[PDB]
Length: 83
Length: 83
Image (cartoon, rainbow over all chains, first blue to last red; front, side):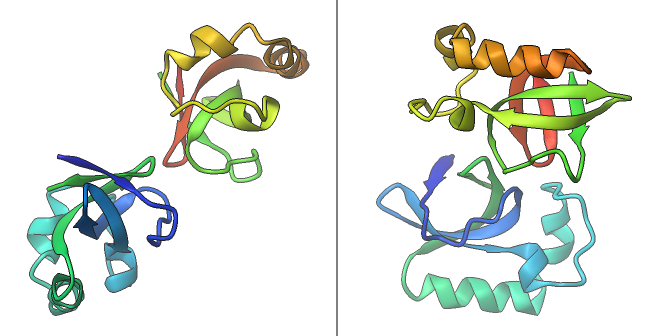
């Protein structure tokens, strides 16, 4: 599933990210490379097997989930794809 | 075919663009949205059917072609893909 990333959502190019989704749009994104500065992968979906249970990723997701449906995925050309 | 975009090549994120290619690298990119400010598409490959014969696009391409192999394509995630 694919969702447009708005212009005030924190977009910063391609990368694995969390997204908050509301009314068919990703209204906030948070990149794995910012949540976890020690992340050194090449943005492969399989990287979430390693990083998805990181306490920093869990904390970032819980903060967004208070307010909107949240999921792990990948950002590319202003679109968020759910993984 | 896909080429890494160089660091001083004019990269500005995602979008339809012309690229000059040298030694398996895109050493200059010029975005359609900058060449033609009236372009208002969603960076679909088919958009080049409308815009590829615009006189501003032909002029930008010929300028680069003087010095390097040039093609129309799409820039995303620091790579250029030929169309």
